[PDB]
Image (cartoon, rainbow, N blue to C red; front, side):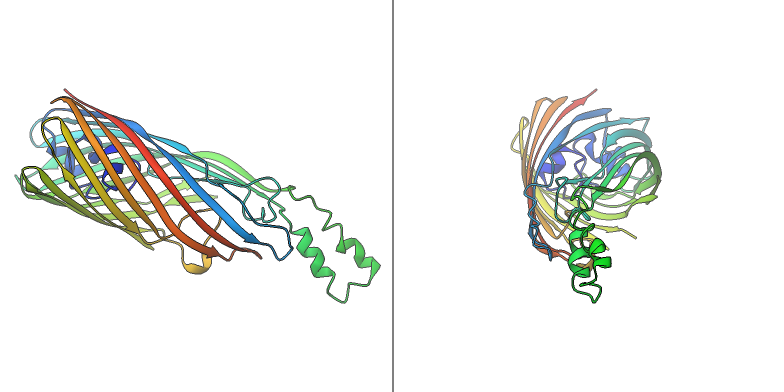
Length: 363
């Protein structure tokens, strides 16, 4: 599930890669290109409104509350698919496969692990798909990712711990130590202690292997590579996804995906259903989960990621066999978990609401 389409949001991004009803999906499964007759164009974006709230106490008395540390964000998509002839087709899309941003105040007791953390990514993908049989089709594409990162950490209340520490050791009474005692408590809870900002482009491929028992049933195996971004170096994780779509009735369908990302450790489970009311109206709903990459001990307050549920419901309105708009609503709720970072002990619990719109035009 990755903000690449309003349609997607609507079905908890379940099945994508095995469902082609809008240029949207080639982005996720090259091979789907071969499922479009005319050349299709889809555009739009999604608006995420998180609600990450940190709570807890420092071993320095200073509080560790950080209400609403996650900022809203807009995520746009550009989707173009067009058939070259009868066995070859190409397509391109501008999408944001990944994006993270949490932000604390200058004076956070624990700003040693929580200044500001913005990391924006943009994906430029150009690709072609091949068809070799009413059933088998293979797609392959190339990606250029633009990564913008900002990292800020402050002294929080370290000096206050370094202090109270020295004011416990035999070097305590000592006034030759008193300096060390304070002078640490002296350090201002906002003294920038980490500033590394920069931009750079990453590259990588991704392939598809759609197979379809017929006009109403298909399964795919997609693969998204690894992307090394050299600033320090950043790594976007490999993503092996398996999905299936079935049109059980003239008016009903079923789509499911089981994704597996390997951050040099996690998977995503989704299932949703579509319902084609008539020529004009369509309605979709999707449920989904996705175990968290982070292993118990190494969690982080700066990276609000943990086992979470997706609950989605969306609707598409086709103007006239050529144009259509989709509306996407998804509500993400990740249960609460305590983090044990640096010398502090926090508790994280944040939800989020997604709203997205896309327009669909075919030639």
